[PDB]
Image (cartoon, rainbow, N blue to C red):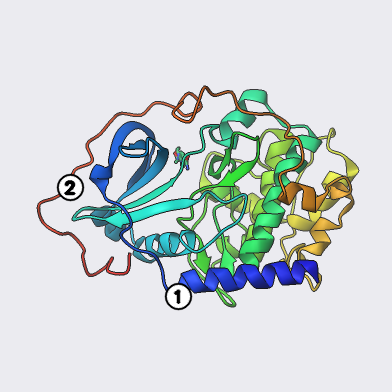
């Protein structure tokens, strides 16, 4: 009942913000630009500093004309409406949002420890206890999101930032969506796509649990289970129902992964009658104190090295491009609700 009441309150609080979203809570000239942390086909993430408070933030900047072109309108509206409504220890917090003639802006807490991806590639692979510490946080985060009828749809090491305490903060809600029942959009990253996405089925939260299997495998092995030069070759392996495990994997890990990387979504852990408890009660998680993880009372496997809230050392170097704002409003109608 403790968990039931926790999730009932979480849903109440989410729905209140979901039905009355915040809007237009800062503006661009409230900030100084520091550094580009990442660049994409329709947006960027910038380290910025608030000129009055001195606080640092990560500012996600989306070009409205490119969002339209790349058919991401609904997705960008999803991202912001969800982020301003959620509240969980392992989700990056949205602090402000606004738009101008050219761009959409989401101003997030800055997490200076960098992407899990960097640390994993630097060390090679994580020990099972280390992988399990991160995986437990994703299990609880999906328990939370799925109870809100949210599917995340972009789990991968690049989207998990490591904070000052060594805990995870999930970033990038660009493909997150509120879904009752099924949804159909092809999105995600190839290595992490569930078979039912590849096969163009109506799919549900089970795709997040598949992706968790991929993530745990990659954390523990150093590479993802389905790998190839071309996406179509990756997709053939995903749909095949065949995975090879390193001999150093524990039997418990292999058993969990066979049940998360279950190609038949009606048999996949997280999508059965017992829901998330099939995962939480699995032998691979026998040492996990779920409440202690939630309360951030567990000592982390490692603390990222960084010098302060403005340190960018754990992010990499990108060409510094203008944040241009047109004299004329672009795509006003499309983004009215943002
Ligand atoms: N909330 C943050 O501190 C943050 C920092 C960097 C970042 N990314 C986007 C993808 O490219 C690499 C940099 N996203 C979010």
Q: Nearer the viewer, residue 170 or 13?
A: 13
Residue corresponding to mark 1: 19
Residue tagged by mark 2? Answer: 325
- Residue drawn at point x = 59 percent, y = 37 percent: 163
Which secondary structure lies at badge 1? helix
Q: Please name the residue shown 69% across and 29% down the image.
A: 302
* Disc 2 residue lies near ligand 1 with CB under 8 A: no
Mark 2, residues whose alpha carbon is within 10 Å: few (<14), some, or many (≥20)? few
Left-right relation of 79 to 115:
left
Q: In the figure, 183 relative to 247: above or below?
A: below
Cβ–Cβ under 8 Å for marks 1 and 2: no
Image coords of residue 130 (percent x, y): 75, 35
Q: Quadrant of residue 121?
A: top right
Whether residue 89 sits left or right of residue 57 in the image: it is right
Q: Quadrant of residue 70?
A: bottom left
Q: Of callouts 1 and 2, which one flags the residue occurring earlier in the amino acid sequence?
A: 1
Q: Which mark is residue 161?
A: none
Pointer 1 local density, CA inside 10 Å: few below 14, some 14–19, many at least 20: few
Among all residues in the image, which is located at the extreme left?
327
Q: Residue at x 37, y 39 (%)?
A: 53
User: Left or right: where does residue 233 sit relative to residue 213?
Assistant: left
Q: Nearer the viewer, mark 1 or mark 2?
A: 1
Residue 161, horizontal then vertical, whole percent: 56, 40
Q: Position of residue 183 (x, y in %)?
A: 53, 72
Residue 201 visible in this rendered orientation of the protein: no
Picture quarter with the N terminus: bottom right
Judging depth in this view, the residue of 1 and 253 nearest the camera is: 1
- Seen in the picture, residue 309 relative to 210 is either above or below; the reply is above
Q: Secondary structure at mark 2?
A: loop
User: Is the C-beta of the residue carrying label 1 under 8 Å from the nearest atom of ligand 1?
Assistant: no
In this view, the residue in front, 3 or 65, is 3
């Amino acid at each position: 009942e403790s968990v039931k009441e926790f999730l009932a309150k979480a849903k109440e609080e989410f729905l209140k913000k979901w039905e009355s979203p915040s809007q237009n809570t800062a503006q661009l000239d409230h900030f100084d630009r520091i550094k580009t942390l990442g660049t994409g086909s329709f947006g960027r993430v910038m380290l910025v500093k608030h000129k009055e408070t001195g606080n640092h933030y990560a500012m996600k900047i989306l070009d409205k004309q490119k969002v339209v072109k790349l058919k991401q309108i609904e997705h960008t509206l999803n991202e912001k409406r969800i982020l301003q409504a959620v509240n969980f220890p392992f989700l990056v917090k949205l602090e402000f949002s606004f738009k101008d003639n050219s761009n959409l802006y989401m101003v997030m807490e800055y997490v200076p420890g960098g992407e899990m991806f960097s640390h994993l590639r630097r060390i090679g692979r994580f020990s099972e206890p280390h992988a399990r510490f991160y995986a437990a946080q994703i299990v609880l985060t999906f328990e939370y999101l799925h109870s809100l009828d949210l599917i995340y749809r972009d789990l991968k090491p690049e989207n998990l930032l490591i904070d000052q305490q060594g805990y995870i903060q999930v970033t990038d809600f660009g493909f997150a969506k509120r879904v009752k029942g099924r949804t159909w959009t092809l999105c995600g990253t190839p290595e992490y796509l569930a078979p039912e996405i590849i096969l163009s089925k109506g799919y549900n939260k089970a795709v997040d649990w598949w992706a968790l299997g991929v993530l745990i495998y990659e954390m523990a092995a150093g590479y993802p289970p389905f790998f190839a030069d071309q996406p179509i070759q990756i997709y053939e392996k995903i749909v095949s129902g065949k995975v090879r495990f390193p001999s150093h994997f524990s039997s418990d890990l292999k058993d969990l992964l066979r049940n998360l990387l279950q190609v038949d979504l009606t048999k996949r852990f997280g999508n059965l009658k017992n829901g998330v408890n099939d995962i939480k009660n699995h032998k691979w998680f026998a040492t996990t104190d779920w409440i202690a993880i939630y309360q951030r009372k567990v000592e982390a496997p490692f603390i990222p090295k960084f010098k302060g809230p403005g340190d960018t050392s754990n992010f990499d170097d990108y060409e510094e491009e203008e944040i241009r704002v047109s004299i004329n409003e672009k795509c006003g109608k499309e983004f009215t609700e943002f």
